[PDB]
Length: 148
Length: 148
Ligand SMILES: [Zn+2]
Ligand SMILES: [Zn+2]
Ligand SMILES: [Zn+2]
Ligand SMILES: [Zn+2]
Ligand SMILES: [Zn+2]
Ligand SMILES: [Zn+2]
Ligand SMILES: [Zn+2]
Ligand SMILES: [Zn+2]
Image 1 (cartoon, rainbow over the protein chains, first blue to last red):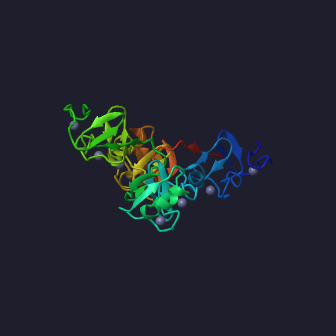
Image 2: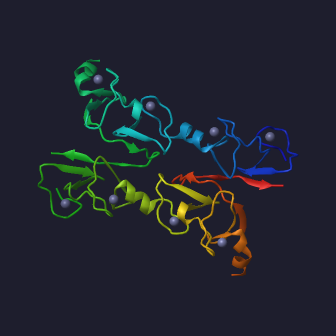
Image 3: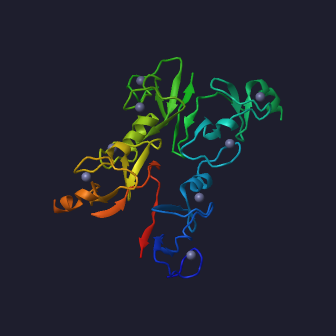
């Protein structure tokens, strides 16, 4: 029994079976936090992850800070970009935007409040800040566009 | 402009564009709760849903009561079956099971506590109740099996 974690073979009282592979239980641990995996685990090909780290790594990224947002965290969004509460802020003045605040979504994800928009376009889609929502962990979503 | 909601055509000041179709804003509403849809909407083919109802309808079902569990709700699970807190109960005595409780998972989803198991097999995989978790809205998951 070769343990796919640490190529020593496996003598232990109890043997783990996962990903059709054989593990010491010390070795079937999260690739990223090295916490031992029980009952189920998540895998990206070759490597195994605990749930937290799988979503941090492979989950929807904050467009501002680029860190993984788990399905658990409430977020702000602009079009198909998603942002942490603390990251949905004007990139020029750094003010945290709020529901009903007028801003512009730039072509690179950048958020610019209305008052700084002349400034940023010298260096844009206008929008009104929507209320936060539970982040939908990447759910194929359809736009609702408006025409007058 | 034929509104795909209510086949009257569309005269309104403002017109909605969604699913490459044209809507009165009164008519681009949730198929199930008839609440008006804004910014994004979710669709199962032909019909459109608000987020709640999409997950209630197309989300992971409680194995006991068969109702849709949104990614937001904490659940109990046995193998690849998921259960509401209030539905992870013995099917014979109706007692709500708790972390560390010994039970059997039957071949039909049915949960039977250890004390009633001789009884239920006359009419089974033994298991120990795991702590509740945030429900993973149907995430492809790998089993960790044990061999002595
Ligand atoms: Zn090992
Ligand atoms: Zn981890
Ligand atoms: Zn962020
Ligand atoms: Zn600003
Ligand atoms: Zn209509
Ligand atoms: Zn609805
Ligand atoms: Zn239920
Ligand atoms: Zn019972």
